[PDB]
């Protein structure tokens, strides 16, 4: 070469701002049966990092992911309406849900993204599973198609851009020709602002909650009554368990899972609710005696 | 011309029920607006036309939009009532001109006025200094309010003209029956060179 | 990706020290080749298994890692030598700074006139602790 | 309202994040400014569940109060844009980024009311500082007064809080694994509630004290109503039935201990039996530690 | 690295991939050339500091200032030389993906073992503005 040759190598990452993610989850779970889709608005820094700052849905038809209610006039109209708010943003990608199963791209899925590849060259297709994502990590990947033609022509070991890694499996269905023929795995990050963090952190307005109140003292004796009688019932069975365990080997006390009502587990289960209650039950009365003295 | 942001200021007042112009000054006001909007959507192919009122607490009935058809359809339902104000109206007009698609449009207010103005000239020529800062053009159409009024608006439109005679001009409409003065005194051919 | 940090960690731990008090060096060396012949170990592991051998034999069994001088002093080229090699936090070609903590510790007899002597050293011990690889 | 058609306004976290994102959209040199959006939501009882919101171009003079602009046409376009994406999303109110109320607000409340009666304000903060929730909800009602002054559009406070869905829950969950709050167990959690509660009463009372001190001197015309209510406060304080109350409160405590005693005792016995189990497992592990 | 130890003849060995005698073709082998030259002449830079300063001063490709910063920082390593510290400082005030990574590292190398308390309050402040996983 007398001049540089085409290049691609890149550890592509997506920042999804704490705002966006919540909208993708919510709106995406709206359509468990018929998955929704949405445009992704934000900026595009250097060339290693997509910055999705915000998203907004698109309408649909009533069968699935049609692109006859993915009107060019919808996204046109909206883009102008968000310029007049104060968002000089452009389309960077398109996300949808594949609820209930693995974060992969289907034939129509692939094909669709191909259109966002002609219209624009920088497109990440981001995937959210509002069902499985529940509680914990939040299953959410990202994918970008890869030129299958160039792969056939000898650039098959030349679709390796320099990404980091962490391995997947259940989507090896279409990821064995996905990761290794049709698309690949981008990696996801977040940006935990301190203002958003001090905002969400709020979940209780207590200046009228506990400590300025306390349950009804006839509602509270009817509670103790019940528990401290259940104590008796469990107690008896507890003696009957302490005679048994002595005369048996731990394999038979191991598989003892018929009527869990007998053992310690329920005297602990109780005492920690009872106590709790009551202690504090306890302090609440005293504290108010001085506070509103 | 260049693409511009036009703001039609129409007035509500008991004075807008005078037979001294075309049947009733109400109806006649409507026709005049209908021509000045249409005539500034053919000068440029694109041009945003507004429509606020100048009475009570000055209000917006339509924001900047290119459809003359909305400007004519809200305008049907006004009513002659209240006492106009010039201050409140102007100042809401800026806030309406800032918000627009595209920042290459020019700021032009087409203002129709029609009842004695009760603000002193000292405050009006402070607002005209703030408009001089904000590069706002303003045409004032005296559809009435020239014999029942000594024009403070003269010192208003000369506070905007340091040297430019198009920067701001106060257009008059003779108070007779004058059918033919509300059509030629239009701001697209009274106080500028263009007439398209 | 923990394996990538425990193969290279071993091959740094052991560069031309052989069977002196750590006989494990034939056990780990085997293991550096165990996972090059395999097509069942991840690329992000293989990359750390190639260097496991590549630094071991570094310099022809002559250079070693030692951040301070045997005189006694922490010389800076070595500190940076293993500080910007270990670092792949985001950049992959940072794998040459390991030539600046490489030192060929050898007695370099220099004659009174800054020229080359001929003179040798008695063995106070057998050639097994002397060592140096065996090409096979 | 007197109507039982409003009471618990419940705002989901993504709204909070949405207004806090809107406050930095405008945020160039137009910051230090009230910014306003419309609240989309659903509701069917004493609730106004807020879910979605989107900024509306809004301006406001910084010394006048009749010079405010709000692109209601923009609303009648977007409102339909979002309806076309989710049915069941009427306009249940509109939010105003604080820091507190402005005289101008009532005006706005009637240019938003041309859509939905019952519209509410939801003052959200752009600065974490309060220890209660940054979400106060007001309604535009009107009333008559005993003094004989003309009817007015005031603003009346209704209780507020934030809730969630599974989606919302999970996203927030995910965003607070840095600031862990789950290491803290039950018992201590509620002691926290009872100290953090005094942290509220303290500053509320403090605010009333600054107000009373404000009218007494450094004059600020008296509003008989405030002082009225402020009398009911000092009649309601628990006092006049002192001796009897004492003799009873002591008794109910006595009970409370009786049951704590029992609780801690059982707890002890059970833990001790646990210890016996450890010792015996240790002996039988010592027979294995020998052998070969 | 393989030819660390060649001094007056290293410019010639690397003259068949270094710029001028070699085409602008693949700026990768030009940037890599400069980086290599900083590896050969690491801590002893004499005429080579000037050579690399003329290679960075007239540079117009991003890859050349990448590998180039990596060579130049090594040749002037442990030194002060306020000229090269400010050239490499301009690389960082230019905000370009792969030029600012290598340039940042190279400026930490130019002032190695010293750092003026002014250069710190320079670099940390510039780290508050910037945005990147490589330059930052």
Image: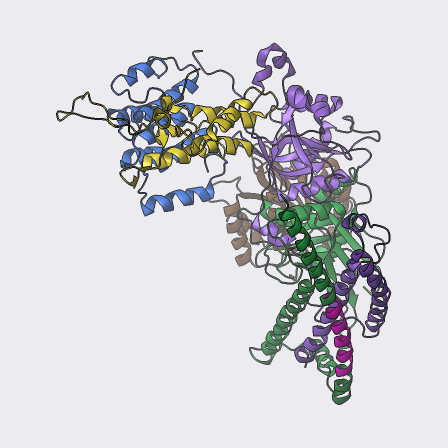
Chain colours: A purple, B brown, C yellow, D green, E blue
Q: Nearer the viewer, residue D230 or D60?
A: D230
Q: Nearer the viewer, residue D73 or A81?
A: A81
Q: Quadrant of the N terminus of chain A?
A: top left
Q: Quadrant of the C terminus of chain A?
A: bottom right
Residue C15 sits inside the magenta stretch? no
Residue A252 percent across, percent down from the top left: 81, 49
**Mainly helix, strand or loop, the magenta region?**
helix
Task: Name the residue at the front extreme.
Answer: D292
In the image: residue E15, left or right of residue B155: left
Vertical side of D255 occupied by A170: above or below: above
Residue D162's image quarter?
A: bottom right
The answer to whether residue B47 of the structure is visible from this angle is yes
Residue range (magenta):
D250-267
Residue D78 percent across, percent down from the top left: 73, 41
Q: How many marks?
A: 0
Residue A292 percent across, percent down from the top left: 68, 79
In the image: residue B166, left or right of residue A286: left
Residue D158's image quarter?
A: bottom right
């Amino acid at each position: 070469p007398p001049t540089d040759a085409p290049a691609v190598d890149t550890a592509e990452q997506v920042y999804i701002s704490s705002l966006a993610l919540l909208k993708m989850l919510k709106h995406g779970r709206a359509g468990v049966p018929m998955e929704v889709m949405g445009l992704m608005l934000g900026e595009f820094v250097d060339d290693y990092t997509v910055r999705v700052i915000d998203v907004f849905a698109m309408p649909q038809s009533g069968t699935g992911v049609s692109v006859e209610a993915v009107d060019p006039v919808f996204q046109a109209k909206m883009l102008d309406m968000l310029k007049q708010t104060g968002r000089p943003e452009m389309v960077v990608g398109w996300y949808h849900s594949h609820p209930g199963f693995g974060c992969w791209l289907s034939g129509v899925d692939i094909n669709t993204q191909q259109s966002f590849e002609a219209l624009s060259e920088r497109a990440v297709a981001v995937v959210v599973d509002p069902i499985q994502s529940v509680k914990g990590k939040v299953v959410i990947d990202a994918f970008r198609l890869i030129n299958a033609n160039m792969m056939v022509l000898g650039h098959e070991p030349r679709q390796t851009t320099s990404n980091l890694g962490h391995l997947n499996k259940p989507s090896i269905q279409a990821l064995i020709h996905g990761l290794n023929r049709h698309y690949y795995s981008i990696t996801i990050n977040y940006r935990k602002n301190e203002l958003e963090q001090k905002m969400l952190l709020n979940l209780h307005k207590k200046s009228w909650m506990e400590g300025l109140t306390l349950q009804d003292y006839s509602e509270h004796c009817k509670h103790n009554e019940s528990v401290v009688k259940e104590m008796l019932e469990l107690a008896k069975n507890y003696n009957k368990a302490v005679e048994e365990e002595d005369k048996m080997t731990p394999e038979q006390l191991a598989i003892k899972n018929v009527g869990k009502q007998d053992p310690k587990r329920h005297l602990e289960e109780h005492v920690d609710v009872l106590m709790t209650s009551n202690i504090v039950q306890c302090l609440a009365a005293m504290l108010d005696t001085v506070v509103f003295k | 011309m260049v693409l511009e942001s036009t703001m039609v200021c129409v007035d509500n007042s008991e004075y807008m029920r005078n037979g001294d112009f075309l049947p009733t000054r109400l109806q006649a006001q409507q026709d005049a607006v209908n021509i000045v909007c249409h005539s500034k959507t053919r000068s440029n192919p694109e041009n945003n036309v507004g429509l606020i009122t100048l009475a009570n607490d000055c209000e917006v009935l339509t924001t900047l939009t290119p459809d003359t058809g909305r400007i004519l359809s809200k305008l049907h339902t006004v009513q002659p009532k209240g006492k106009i104000t010039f201050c409140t109206g102007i100042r809401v007009a800026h806030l309406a001109l800032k918000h627009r698609q595209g920042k290459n449009h020019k700021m032009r207010i087409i203002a129709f006025v029609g009842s004695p103005v009760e603000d002193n000239e000292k405050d009006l020529v402070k607002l005209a200094k703030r408009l001089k800062k904000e590069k706002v053009n303003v045409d004032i159409i005296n559809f009435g309010e020239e014999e029942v009024n000594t024009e403070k608006l003269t010192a208003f439109v000369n506070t905007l003209n340091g040297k430019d005679g198009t920067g701001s001009h106060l257009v008059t409409v003779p108070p007779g029956p004058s059918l033919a003065d509300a059509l030629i005194s239009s701001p697209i051919l009274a106080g500028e060179g263009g007439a398209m | 990706y923990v394996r990538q940090g425990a193969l290279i960690a071993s091959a740094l731990i052991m560069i031309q020290q052989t069977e002196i008090t750590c006989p494990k060096v034939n056990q780990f060396r085997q293991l550096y080749s165990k996972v090059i012949n395999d097509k069942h170990d991840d690329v992000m592991a293989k990359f750390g298994a190639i260097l496991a051998q590549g630094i071991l034999d570094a310099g022809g069994h002559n250079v070693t890692i030692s951040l301070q001088s045997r005189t006694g002093h922490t010389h800076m080229p070595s500190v940076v030598g293993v500080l910007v090699f270990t670092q792949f936090w985001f950049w992959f070609p940072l794998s040459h700074f390991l030539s600046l903590a490489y030192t060929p510790t050898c007695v370099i007899g220099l004659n009174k006139d800054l020229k080359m002597p001929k003179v040798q050293y008695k063995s106070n011990c057998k050639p097994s602790t002397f060592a140096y690889p065996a090409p096979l | 309202m007197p109507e039982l058609a409003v009471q618990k306004v419940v705002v989901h976290p993504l709204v909070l994040l949405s207004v806090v994102d809107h406050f930095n959209r405008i945020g160039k040199v137009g910051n230090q400014k009230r910014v306003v959006g419309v609240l989309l939501g659903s509701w069917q009882k004493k609730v106004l569940d807020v879910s979605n919101s989107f900024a509306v171009p809004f301006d406001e003079d910084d010394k006048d109060d009749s010079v405010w602009f709000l692109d209601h046409d923009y609303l009648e376009n977007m409102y339909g844009m979002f309806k076309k994406v989710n049915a069941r999303e009427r306009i249940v109110g509109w939010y105003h980024t604080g820091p507190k109320l402005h005289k101008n607000d009532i005006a706005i409340n009637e240019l938003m009311k041309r859509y939905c009666p019952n519209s509410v304000l939801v003052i959200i903060d752009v600065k974490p500082k309060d220890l209660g929730l940054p979400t106060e909800a007001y309604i535009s009602v009107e009333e008559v007064h005993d003094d004989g002054t003309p009817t007015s559009k005031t603003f009346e406070h209704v209780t507020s809080e934030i809730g969630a869905e599974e989606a919302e829950e999970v996203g927030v969950e995910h965003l607070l694994r840095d600031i862990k709050d789950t290491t803290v167990g039950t018992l201590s959690q509620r002691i926290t509630n009872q100290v953090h509660g005094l942290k509220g009463l303290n500053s509320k009372l403090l605010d009333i004290r600054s107000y009373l001190e404000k009218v007494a001197t450094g004059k600020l015309p008296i509003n008989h109503q405030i002082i009225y209510q402020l009398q009911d406060v000092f009649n309601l304080l628990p006092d006049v039935s002192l001796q009897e109350f004492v003799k009873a409160f002591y008794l109910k405590t006595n009970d409370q201990m009786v049951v704590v005693y029992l609780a801690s005792l059982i707890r002890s016995v059970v833990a001790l039996h646990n210890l016996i189990n450890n010792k015996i497992a240790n002996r039988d592990a010592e027979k294995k530690e020998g052998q070969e | 690295v393989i030819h660390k130890g060649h001094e007056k003849e290293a410019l010639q060995l690397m003259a068949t991939y270094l710029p001028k005698d070699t085409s602008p073709g693949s700026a990768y082998q030009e940037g890599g050339g400069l980086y290599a030259l900083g590896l050969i002449h690491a801590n002893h830079g004499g005429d080579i500091i000037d050579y690399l300063l003329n290679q960075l001063k007239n540079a117009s490709n991003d890859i050349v200032r990448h590998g180039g910063s990596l060579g130049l920082g090594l040749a002037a390593m442990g030194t002060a030389r306020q000229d090269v510290y400010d050239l490499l400082k301009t690389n960082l005030y230019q905000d370009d993906a792969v030029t600012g990574e290598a340039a940042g590292l190279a400026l930490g190398l130019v002032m190695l073992g010293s750092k003026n308390a002014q250069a710190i309050e320079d670099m940390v402040g510039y780290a508050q503005e910037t945005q990147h996983e490589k330059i930052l």
